[PDB]
Amino acid sequence: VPVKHVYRVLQCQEEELTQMVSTMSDGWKFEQLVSIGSSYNYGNEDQAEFLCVVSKELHNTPYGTASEPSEKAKILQERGSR
Amino acid sequence: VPVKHVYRVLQCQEEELTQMVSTMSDGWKFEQLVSIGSSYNYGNEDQAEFLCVVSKELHNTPYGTASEPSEKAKILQERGSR
Amino acid sequence: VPVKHVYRVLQCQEEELTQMVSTMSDGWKFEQLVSIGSSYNYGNEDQAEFLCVVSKELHNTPYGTASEPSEKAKILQERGSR
Amino acid sequence: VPVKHVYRVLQCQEEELTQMVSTMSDGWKFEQLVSIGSSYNYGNEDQAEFLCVVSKELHNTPYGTASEPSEKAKILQERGSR
Amino acid sequence: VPVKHVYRVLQCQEEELTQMVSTMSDGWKFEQLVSIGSSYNYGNEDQAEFLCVVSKELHNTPYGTASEPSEKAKILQERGSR
Amino acid sequence: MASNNTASIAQARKLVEQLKMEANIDRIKVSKAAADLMAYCEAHAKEDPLLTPVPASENPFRE
Amino acid sequence: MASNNTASIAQARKLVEQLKMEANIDRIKVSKAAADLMAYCEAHAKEDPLLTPVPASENPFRE
Amino acid sequence: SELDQLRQEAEQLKNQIRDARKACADATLSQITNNIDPVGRIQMRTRRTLRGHLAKIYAMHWGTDSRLLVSASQDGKLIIWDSYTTNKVHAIPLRSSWVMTCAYAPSGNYVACGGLDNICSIYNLKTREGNVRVSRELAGHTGYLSCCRFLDDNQIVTSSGDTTCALWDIETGQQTTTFTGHTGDVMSLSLAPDTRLFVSGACDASAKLWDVREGMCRQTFTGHESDINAICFFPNGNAFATGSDDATCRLFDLRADQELMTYSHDNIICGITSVSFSKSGRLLLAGYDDFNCNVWDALKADRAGVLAGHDNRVSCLGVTDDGMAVATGSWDSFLKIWN
Amino acid sequence: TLRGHLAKIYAMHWGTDSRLLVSASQDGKLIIWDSYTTNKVHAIPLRSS
Amino acid sequence: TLRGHLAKIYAMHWGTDSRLLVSASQDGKLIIWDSYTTNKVHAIPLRSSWVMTCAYAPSGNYVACGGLDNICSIYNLKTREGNVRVSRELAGHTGYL
């Protein structure tokens, strides 16, 4: 059976870009870097403009993933989804 | 037999990007992010600015891929391309 | 022998992009989407705004290497080369 | 064998871009290359134009990992991380 | 057993893109298109549009360790290294 | 099984020692505890910029 | 043997032995060493680029 | 038991060395003859901004062609800068991050680098295939490499933890001479222009000078009250300047085996991180822990000038093999050439 | 202010050096923040959400 | 000017058609420029960099390359598959071409 993938995106400034790229491990493979543009003034003081999309794989794929939410945690997800 | 990959394009704005990538479906792999501008201006404002392209590797190809069609589906899908 | 790869480029609008990507053929992997403009607009609302590079893998050892080239085939290739 | 991928990000303008990709070091895989519109020297021919994300895989179980402690080294990590 | 890779960048105009991508030599895998602009205007009248990074996989892992550069080849390498 | 009441009697038993052990804990009048809290708070009032303004320097999150 | 603290007499021997050749270092006057450094500085004070700036056609940072 | 006599001889001979130093001590002629016209203000200018790095720069070294400088960054990349064009001749990523040292070969053919990997990797820049390849990964240390220097293209000396400065023969891949005798780990190393004697400073506030032909430690110097940070020989090759985490720099002379001169000033409270003489040896260009570094008059012990650039601390100083310019590797990911 | 998260924060804790925060997000990011410069010292993705 | 190379060009050779000109670069690019329109007919990557030779066959179907690889690679431009291919790789020199 094909392995299932878990994906995350990290937000990067120009200076911390190199650090965060070089300081990942344990299967957190780089997938794609993209440039948002600054969440601040454009053309001056440009900071925090990168997204790094990373991924990893479930090694124990035959064991797989199963869902059984906690009874309290359902209302917590309900409160957290909206 | 070499596997088939089915591809989808799902289109998101700036903020939703993290929510959609993190909650990617179980089997769907991430392929690409591309950025478009906006109708107001390129690379500015919140209308929509990203096209996630994703793929799934169909593993049940050696179980067959042909299906029995119907004429009503044929005319409906002919109209769909119109 | 290590497999060969045949690459193609598909021009895309924003309307046509999802249709064409979801209707990619069997064995054709999606490689990369890039966004362009022509002279006036770049991104949305243009008549040429996406290039989709796709690939196919030639698993079988023979791929039409030679059959016996006729005389006029070379002249046609020369005509199309310029 | 589980494999870890070491990732780095190099920086180059287009003058040395070809030289760096062509002479990319032994065993380092080109992952992706991003272009940044530089506010200094109008984009091109500025040193921060292009970032190349590179990587290599390590057969860790044959080789192993490093966990050797050192007090002064720990002080250096403390200073560097802040 | 790890395998060496060789990376090149092929500069192209927007018009030339499809012909080269379709006519990529055997064994040369496609890696990435990256767009560029000019120093005075991007989106129109661009004399350098795309860089297509391509890669080739060098099959012969046990290539050996025997070589002997010519006496004055070092002079050419030194002169071309500047 | 049902006659064993699913060891719910066991639950009952482990309910008991929880409270009596609570009864065995000595209590200190709320007056003395409030006195300790009042004194410790008054002693520490001068520091902790969270309450009082501090110069621009010596403030790690401004200068 | 660990009873003698693991033959630490050996390492003490080695470190003191290091001190003997520190007693074999022949010591010369500070004055003429200062004079030597002073004279070398004065003899190289006119060709040092970091004392007198050479002109724009000689350094490779303004050409 | 009998261990008492051993330390008794230790302290009595140590007293004998201090007595020999004091008896042979004389007035230092340099600052009495401070009558050399003051250099006034030497306005050194930041002329190149080697901004291709992105992480903090931990080490930089010039080559023997005085054109190419190797610079190491925290993330684990070396950059060979052609300082006359602000273009990277090569950009070598490293398998291991947190590189502390980088060395340029005396021929420009090889480059050494190492760090908390506890391994000194040697990259061969010049090969007919093109790209840079690692030649030998010298292993055998158990501490972190802190400085690296080439005697030649086949011998290297590597200061690191474990209090060892083992000299590696590159082709064999094994260290031949193990320099041991420090009590705190050695974290600096400077090669003489004579390439037979080298000094290594440790975090035990001592700088030991060793001869490369055998394994014994020739001399030991102690004038600092805190861990040494970097050393740099005098151009002549019989003196060296050494800074520490204290705000005082100290110039030692081998011909006298005692501290010859001291540099300090009340404004600086931040430690030294790098030291570098000019061609004539009148300028002490030392790297501080402050955002800006200063140059002393290396004979008269007064503030010669400032390098008022950089946003964060400087970490390494390097002068060319002909003294034409100087580079200030610094944590703001910019190397600045000063001239 | 600290801005390196895109999902809702569910927890945060200070270090014993009172400079480094650990911020936990819905998607599975633990961002180790240096608060004196708003410079995110790490950004650890989590295999769980 | 036939800009489009991005590394140092080390050799060139016109064809016998006075239309196509090969350009070999250090990076490992053979660009077969169409001189009149400044359009590259072919952009052949090469296995080894430091290429310093390139010869056009006097028929326009073959091209040659060589350098520090010590190998003369012969590329076939006219094939029914469209893409350029290595027809042969001549080896036997211990030096550079």
Image: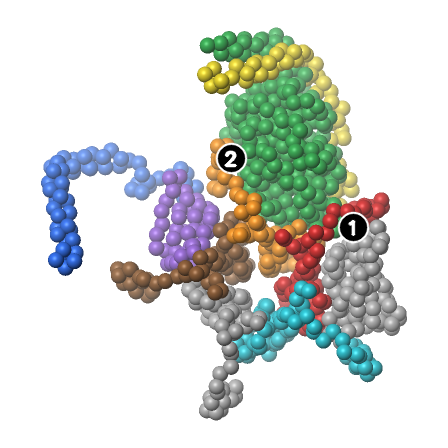
Chain colours: A brown, C cyan, D orange, E red, F blue, G yellow, H green, I purple
In front of the other: A44 or A60: A60
Q: CA distance from mark 1 to mark 2?
A: 41 Å
Q: Quadrant of residue H84?
A: top right
Q: Position of residue A46 (x, y in %)?
A: 52, 56
Q: Position of residue C8 (x, y in %)?
A: 65, 73
Q: Position of residue H290 (x, y in %)?
A: 53, 35
Q: Position of residue H265 (x, y in %)?
A: 54, 26
| Residue at image point 81% right, 82% down | C70
Left or right side of F18 for D81: right
* Disc 2 target residue: D73
Q: Secondary structure at mark 1?
A: helix
Instruction: Report crowding for label 1: few under 14, some 14 to 19, many 20 or more residues within 10 A (C-alpha).
Output: few
Same chain for labels 1 and 2? Say yes or no.
no
In front of the other: G47 or H15: H15
Q: Residue type at mark 2?
A: Ala
Q: Which subunit holds the residue at mark 2?
A: D
| Residue at image point 15% right, 47% down | F14
Which dot marks residue E80?
Answer: 1
* Closer to the eye: label 1 or 2: 2
